[PDB]
Image (tube, coloured by chain):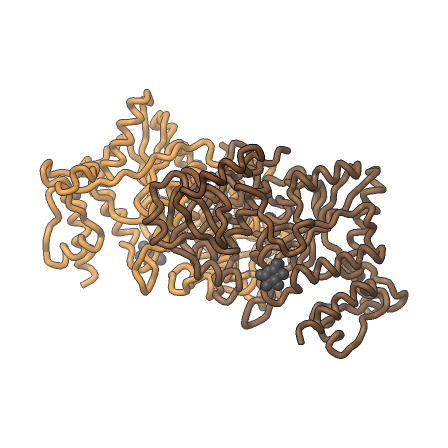
Chain colours: A orange, B brown
Amino acid sequence: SDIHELFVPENKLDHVRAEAETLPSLSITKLDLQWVQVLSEGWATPLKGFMREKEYLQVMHFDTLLDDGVINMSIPIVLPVSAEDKTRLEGCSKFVLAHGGRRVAILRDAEFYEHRKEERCSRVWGTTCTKHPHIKMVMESGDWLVGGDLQVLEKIRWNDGLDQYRLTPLELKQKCKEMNADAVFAFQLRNPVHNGHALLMQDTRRRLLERGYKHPVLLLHPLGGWTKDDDVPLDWRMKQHAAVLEEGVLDPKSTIVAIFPSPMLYAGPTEVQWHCRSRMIAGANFYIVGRDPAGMPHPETKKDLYEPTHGGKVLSMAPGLTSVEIIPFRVAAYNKAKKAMDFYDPARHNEFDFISGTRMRKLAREGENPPDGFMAPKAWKVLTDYYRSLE
Amino acid sequence: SDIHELFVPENKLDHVRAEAETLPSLSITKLDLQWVQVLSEGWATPLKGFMREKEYLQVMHFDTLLDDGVINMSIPIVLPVSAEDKTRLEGCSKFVLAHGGRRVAILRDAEFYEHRKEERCSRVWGTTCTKHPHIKMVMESGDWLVGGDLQVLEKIRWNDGLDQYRLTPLELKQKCKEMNADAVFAFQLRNPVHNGHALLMQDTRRRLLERGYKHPVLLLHPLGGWTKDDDVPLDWRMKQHAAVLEEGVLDPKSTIVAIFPSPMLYAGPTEVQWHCRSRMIAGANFYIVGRDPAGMPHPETKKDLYEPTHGGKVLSMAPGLTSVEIIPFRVAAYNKAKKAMDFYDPARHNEFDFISGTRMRKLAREGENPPDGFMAPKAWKVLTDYYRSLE
Ligand SMILES: OC[C@H]1O[C@@H](O)[C@H](O)[C@@H](O)[C@@H]1O
Ligand SMILES: OC[C@H]1O[C@@H](O)[C@H](O)[C@@H](O)[C@@H]1O
């Protein structure tokens, strides 16, 4: 239940920042900096920094963290570095990480070890398909990894108008306490919210009320780190979600909308454990699985990279998630009879019309609306503005 | 710990055999039959048969078996089937497995699930390199897997003159008991034994005696399931090991020589867990790691597929191996100062000369002998007969 943040104390920051100007420095990428944000805020509690070699091995082979207890940790959080930089910095026991001209953190007692890229991609993604857009970034990175104790100077801000939504796990716990929450149920997502998603979240709220929880709180938690090129961008998704809440499709008085700062791997059942354990750190006792969670189509062939039931099955078997209950995904679809979203029943297959993201883009392209009741009208209007902005 | 064998009771065999002639049958390969042998003898205790879907997933993602407790199980033991055979047998709750005209086992309450071959190879081997000889067998197998409860009619014999060495875990425990063993230390291997290997085993015996064990027993345990084309064949290796024992380089009075019936995957750190946990089932309290354990050169390039320290590091971190102590590998080499083998010390680098398997084959090719003290003379003569037999 403890959260291990990695920030310098407030009262020491001005002095610490002043001194770090003298240390040798290592330039990191934007993706690396998003991982520094993830580490800094305690999402990967109790990691002390970028993973050392033994931590990396245990994650890759067992999906658990080096610890006297059992802690779920299924994805590597590692910092790739060039051979040149390894040569320069090995044996330096205290150096700075910098990005965009700013010194953002100090890495202490660093160790350098081989980045065996093909093995990492095979074991984490279950493929080494070079066209996968996140695998491509790993394959292009340096041949070494550096792990160590990380101390982060201050909260990583992006200054894009969305930092107000980038809450830390501690801040989310404080917000839930202010709402007198006695159940926190989380929904991970990377797409617009339609009324089938909403139906799932409303069904979960209803089920928790019937169990006797007095104040269940929905944590609507869109991912906002690196995503692939064909996802709707984060700022447009936040506008769309805001429209859903303003329409009352989800109730603002029992919902927290916040951005989860992690890069997305699109690693299917390996990554859904990460999506779950991070919401657990933020206090969620309940986790709603999505459709094809963390999945994507195999490039070139367009067939599903992962088997669509494996995320839920693996999450149900995973070690170190004892404090969270998995809420199964339930297919919803537009019911032509009720003119409304409803849970799908194969015993009534012919009543239901499915609407995918490609369908929505094609609908906007012809200036069409989806069926009435598929999406809150102001939220649909946000999406048509997005597609229009693509000209 | 209990061993869960899968054999039909003695008193029932003649009856069950007579009945199984009427059941629908599924033809399995030689490799499959070697896995039936592994399963039947309890090496994969407490597996009940070929892995069901949820067992398979937990193995691939977590290296542990579906459990009430935590049990190490890092490799899939699965039965591939063609789509035609799946169509024929799904819903059949009791059918036989057959090979070479013999009905060898009954599979009960079978379930069929997709063989996602690329994902299996990526997660288990950390590569999908097609040319890896065991990966090629997986890639060429059927598109379905079948799991279920397996009942094996009788001990799988190969009738090649080596069945006397293929002892079950129960038989190994009984043999150790007959020797009044109070420590059993196991050495996995797939190659000839030279006097560096022997030095490691003799040093381990010495250390166990100094800890106060009165009767430590060496389990010299060559693997004898499927191996790749360029390994010395099993019958030649057993002749070579017998020569080492007859020369007294290892003491027959405190050594058990037996054949471990598992196919070899050559999957490095994933497979060394399997090599260790199987010896644990047979009662080994101590497990000596070899050099580059379960490794092989990447085909085409010929560099090491795995990082040579990872097998020992991963084994030290693995869950479910609490009752085994890992004895670290120590490099030995031919010391030119004296002439015996000796543990390598970089501080005396120039005294030592290494002798690989390629070096031994080239030595035989020119009719040359290795240095005096590298290998027992009778055992070297076995190897020169082997190399000569390939003309
Ligand atoms: O998810 C945050 C951002 O990540 C970038 O990698 C994507 O290209 C953007 O569209 C997205 O808004
Ligand atoms: O290890 C048992 C046998 O397996 C076969 O696959 C190899 O080709 C033989 O050389 C070996 O003796």
A219 vs B213, nearest the viewer: B213
* Residue B164 at x, y percent in the picture: 69, 49
Q: Is residue B97 left or right of residue B292?
A: left
Q: Quadrant of the C terminus of chain A?
A: bottom left
| Residue at 46% from the left image edge and 54% from the top image edge | B120
**Residue furthest to the bottom:** B366
Residue B391 appearing in the image: yes
A370 vs B69, nearest the viewer: B69
* Residue B307 at x, y percent in the picture: 61, 60
Task: State ligand 2's quadrant.
Answer: bottom right
| Residue at 48% from the left image edge and 53% from the top image edge | B101
A1 vs B105, nearest the viewer: B105
**Number of marks present in the image shown:** 0
Q: Is residue A143 left or right of residue A196?
A: right
Q: Is residue A151 above or below residue B12?
A: below
Residue A11 appearing in the image: no
Q: Is residue A224 above or below residue B213?
A: below
**Residue furthest to the top:** A212
| Residue at 47% from the left image edge and 57% from the top image edge | B121
Q: Is residue B271 left or right of residue A354?
A: right
* Residue A20 at x, y percent in the picture: 57, 54
* Residue B265 at x, y percent in the picture: 56, 56
